Amino acid sequence: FVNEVRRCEEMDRKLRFVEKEIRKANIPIMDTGENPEVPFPRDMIDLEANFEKIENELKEINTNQEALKRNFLELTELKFILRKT
Amino acid sequence: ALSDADVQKQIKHMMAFIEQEANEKAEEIDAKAEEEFNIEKGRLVQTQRLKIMEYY
Amino acid sequence: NIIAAKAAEVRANKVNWQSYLQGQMISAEDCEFIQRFEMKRSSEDKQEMLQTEGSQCAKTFINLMTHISKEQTVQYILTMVDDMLQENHQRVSIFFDYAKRSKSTAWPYFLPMLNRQDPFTVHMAARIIAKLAAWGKELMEGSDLNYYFNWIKTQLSSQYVQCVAGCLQLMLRVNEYRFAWVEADGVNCIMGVLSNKCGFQLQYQMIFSIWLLAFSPQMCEHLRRYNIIPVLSDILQESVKEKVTRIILAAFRNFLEKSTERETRQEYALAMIQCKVLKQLENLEQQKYDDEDISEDIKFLLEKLGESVQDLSSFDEYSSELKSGRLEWSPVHKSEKFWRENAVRLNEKNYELLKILTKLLEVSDDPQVLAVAAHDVGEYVRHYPRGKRVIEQLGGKQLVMNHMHHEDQQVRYNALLAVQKLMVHN
Amino acid sequence: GTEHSGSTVPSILNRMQTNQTPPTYNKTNKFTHGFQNIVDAYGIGTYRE
């Protein structure tokens, strides 16, 4: 049964990734309540895989906007070089 | 009884489990045996139909 | 459990057949066979049933079953006969009790019968109807059984229904009559009962009958028109009961190994498009089982599904549909190998494919085809910075900028991804 | 649980005796937990003590 635990650890790693991301973003946590809400399907594994895909494209958006700002860092330089004669 | 009745219930459910499981297994073996049957019969028809066609 | 409970209930009841061996009330002669062969475990008895020559065996017992007919009287006589007809491990086997002089013993006696489908009467009738597959006697008329209510009224109402369907699945073995039943609308009824919610045992029986019907290549090809493969993958996703997964896997295996015509096997691509069964297999492989069938079939299906997706990954039909403008979400679009090696094929004469996709993006308003085309263009421009200059010269960047602000935020997000792949070095 | 996921599971339970020492336990509340903690700070003793 160790495979289930390994998949859970992967799930934990992805959840930590998003956690540290939202802590860098500094978005206040809601925590409405609902402690007794535990369900018992087997299908939520697919749903959490989908949310890990959401986290993957989030990692893409970060690794992409960092490139965008780097591009701007030379765009502004080109503008300044243009301002002169 | 309660404890002995539970033991009897457990025995009955275990018998039901073996019954269903290996009954389905037995029919699965027989269905494989039908596929088996038809494949070998087809090969046989090919082999004999050959000689039939030349002779005729 | 109702039928087994009834059988156990009336097994112990010993009828007074000796009070009228050949005596009062119940007839007066047909207890000469009953007195013989009372020891069912006796080799001598099971081999000397042939001494009867059928004269009493299932000749007078036939129409004695109608002689007695009371909810108490004929319920006891009914079981005391049909429990012997049911055990039948090697006693009759290949129709030893023959009764050649009259055909009614073989088949036509149940027309008045098939009544009161609850006090075991339809159950005995179905059991004697269940004397074809492992018994040597060819049914005189398939429609004399396929079109009678013995199953029709039991479809909806449950252990009696389960036992009826058990007799049915025991009988559906040899194609000579399964074809006769498939020509009827029985396929539609099987599909409807499948869609109907019920106990998991009944659902297993239904998929089991489907697996039995899967034997026939040409009739599977004829019944391609129904959406059985996705309804079955859907119930597979909805239920995990081990034996059910095994039988569904065996049915898919049967389809793949029969495969009458590759041209008619358009369902090869459906098996992933309609629902990625490979995603379910990705988990089911991790669970190991002692049954060699499960492991061998899952390995064989993984390999064959790999071949299927690899063959599906192509450029010819891809460019055909991209030209026609019908852009469904095929998994070939995301196939990395297409853009690693086959990327230059999109560069047709004068970049015909890219320009016509720009035109179709300008024309069509459908969010999903717009998304598909935009993603394809983005993944193409991801690797060819020269074609990036070509696209910039064409001016499609302005089209993507216009489609960025759009009612479908999904199209907006994909447009942002495409414009970003253009922002690579730009 | 069985009616949550119904598959004819009686969930049978049997009682048996042995020599293994059962573990100690004492229900507490919001105004005895501190004292239970202080007393268990020096270990917990034998069964039915």
Image (cartoon, coloured by chain):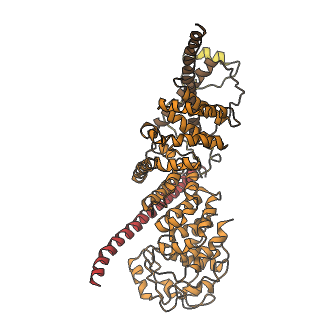
Q: Residue furthest top?
A: A85
Residue at point 55%, 18% (across, down): A71
**x, y percent for residue C153:** 67, 70
Q: Quadrant of the C terminus of chain C?
A: top right
Give the side of residue C291 with respect to residue C364, left or right.
Answer: left
Please determine whether, in this image, residue D48 is positioned above or below residue C145.
above
**x, y percent for residue C99:** 48, 88
Give the side of residue C195 with respect to residue C314, left or right.
Answer: right
Please determine whether, in this image, residue C5 is positioned above or below residue A47.
below
Shown in brown, the chain is: A
Please determine whether, in this image, residue C16 is positioned above or below residue C247.
below
Quarter of the rendering containing residue C158: bottom right
Shown in yellow, the chain is: D
**x, y percent for residue C251:** 49, 58
Shown in orange, the chain is: C
Q: Nearer the viewer, residue C407 or B51?
A: C407
Display colour for chain B:
red
